[PDB]
Every structure is written in C-alpha cells, then in structure tokens.
Length: 133
Length: 133
Image (cartoon, rainbow over all chains, first blue to last red):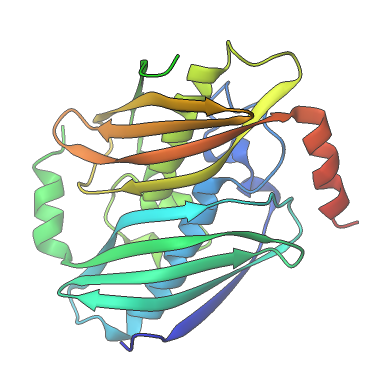
C-alpha cells in the first residue's frame, strides 16, 4: 500500500445503528437519544480500513484493530449518510496506521487515528481457541 | 470523585463478535469470533455512564465525545470482560476518564475516554434539526 492513499466508504445510518442497539442488554442505554453510537462509528471506520487493505493481503492473512483514537463531535440521526475517509499514514512491519475522518453530510462528526496489525488467521485462530472457556 | 475506581463486568456472548457489529459487512462476516473493538468502546462508555448516573440531575444524560484506547488481546465469547473506569477530572460539563479492560486472562486494552453532560431533551431537539423528513 502507499502512504497517503485515501479510501472512502459511505453508509446511510439505519434505525438499528443507534446507541440502544449497540447494547440492548443495557438498561443504562435505553434512555439515550436515537443517535449513531460511537462504537458503530468506530466499526465503520475500521470497516473502511479493512476494505482498503484487502487487495494487499496474502491468502491466509487477516487483520486486527489494535488501537482507536478518535473524537466524536456531532451527533447523527438515522437517515443521514456517514462518509468515512481513511488515509494511510504509516506502515511499520505488520502494522498500519490510518488517519480516519467521518462526516454525516451536515457536520463533521469525528476523526482521529486507527492502527491495525496483519495476522495469520489460523495461528491466531489456534490462540483464540486456547483462551476459550 | 476523582481517583475513584468503578468496575464493570460483562460476560461476552456470541452476539458481540465482529460479524455482529456490522451484519451488513461481508468483510466482517468471516472475521474470527472475537469481541469487536466497537463493542469494547461501547462497554467502556457503559462503565463510565453507570459511574455517573447518580450524579446527574433530572433530565440530564451524557455523550461520549472522545475515546483513545489500545486493543491488545482478543476475547472469545464466554470470558467476562471487566472494565475499570477511573475518573480523572470534572471540568464544567466535561468528565474525563482513564479506562482499562481485562478478560480474566489478559488485559485487552486501556486508554482514555471523555464524556459531556447534556440536557436530554435540549439535545434530542438539536438532533431533530438534522433529522431528515
């Protein structure tokens, strides 16, 4: 991949992408305004980066999100399009760093950085299998 | 009060794995069955929200306005993730936190989280202004 490369990913926010939907298990969240959850924003940012990386992964490889550092500065109701822009900022070993940003057509809603590590799925799968209850 | 450690325990169910974050995403649908960064962020917000609720006034709620955390080990369903939230400061409407999370086997992440106290209906209305007809 090339440092500086950009990718864009558009997402119309549905009704099941609001705060209460990230954790139906939470009574503490049932009171919240019907807005796009930060956790769902984080997911959409990761998703953009994943799509950007996909062409460049050898067979048997995947990636994990290893860090997320973002602000969430405006709220987004269902119906608006969230556009995430992902810009590759640096690569070092199995590690990639992206500058990510998100706009909902009306406001910039957040931005920051996201780090991923390329992994070998089946070695990783074995490890996650030995931590399994 | 500042320095106070609030603990929050959560048994990870199958429906908090990566593919469950975005069932819309074909990319996520093949990911390993591990607790998603986006769900960890929501869990960290949940811990802080519970820690705050006593202290809000009627009609008050809060929103996460920033998150900056690592995600350093993977968690299969069945483990309990314990979030530890510690209050760093209260400045006006802003509450600042150090958060960390552990799955009973490894520490899985840590960093910082900020939240803003809001007037629930006063905010819901602002969101209406952005809500498409």
